[PDB]
Length: 158
Length: 158
Ligand SMILES: O=c1ccn([C@@H]2O[C@@H]3COP(=O)(O)O[C@H]3[C@H]2O)c(=O)[nH]1
Image 1 (cartoon, protein in one colour):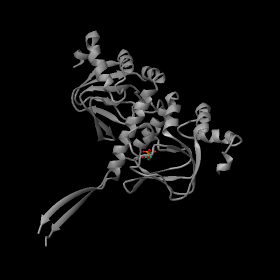
Image 2: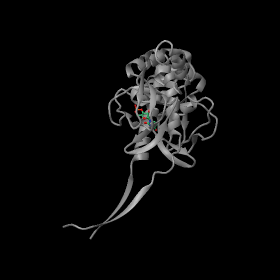
Image 3: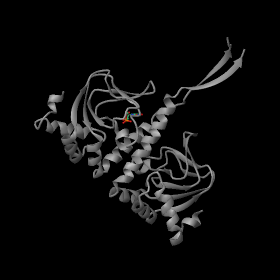
Image 4: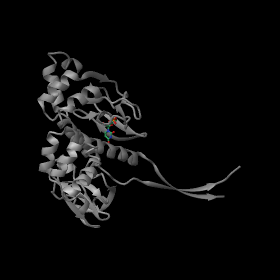
């Protein structure tokens, strides 16, 4: 789908794409500035765009496809069109990637570096706000009960 | 407690407890302005500062004491001094309280209205960034609980 979004002719639909992103929420100003600063990447199915406990700090705006969020071997969510990933490392200068993010399928993403993002968010506070809202949602979702497994051990030494 | 932080005499100790807040991160200008627009309240052991599915939207900076965070009858966290509460209902303005907040002992909290907080934060990007950062930290701790395998061992030796 890249070719639709590439170049000056692609900009009309690149800006609208980024307007639909949950972190942008329709703001043309942020979308236009974001459009100037992102780089388009395709992601192969099964690719780990982000790996847990690595020290990348890029943010990805998901235009197309979907990705597994995996912590310590277990999937805890999936993220699809108009979602974002990598914001947690981008707003915390000393935190490693909290999760592996793996393409369930072929995806198209807009990548922005921490340096370009922090410079934009500096004077577009509402990006920090909209990130907070997303993190609030992830926090408020399906707490359920963490199971304790009970084991009885009969130990024999040789 | 409240005596220490009230009036001109108290302002030095009030600003100091405020600039120590997880949301203020040592910034003096923000602490000084916060102080100008908070009301100190004593919260008593047992008193529900905030009730789940209620529609208050004040933010509280915890200066002294600690409080239970409760979702549908059962606790999920404790917030101590330098924490805050009610920050989500000043980030999602159309949303009821997500949790009850019951004081575990006598507390001194600083209450600011949504109106005053929003006005302050609007020209002070860092408050929204600070909120995002603490929500990211809390989601990290949750990723860890949810994906940690919890095991209860009973060992018999022969
Ligand atoms: O409950 C959730 C839902 C989504 N995520 C994402 O995993 C990403 C991993 O890298 P990061 O730490 O820079 O950013 C993270 C988030 O975007 C998560 O960690 N937990």
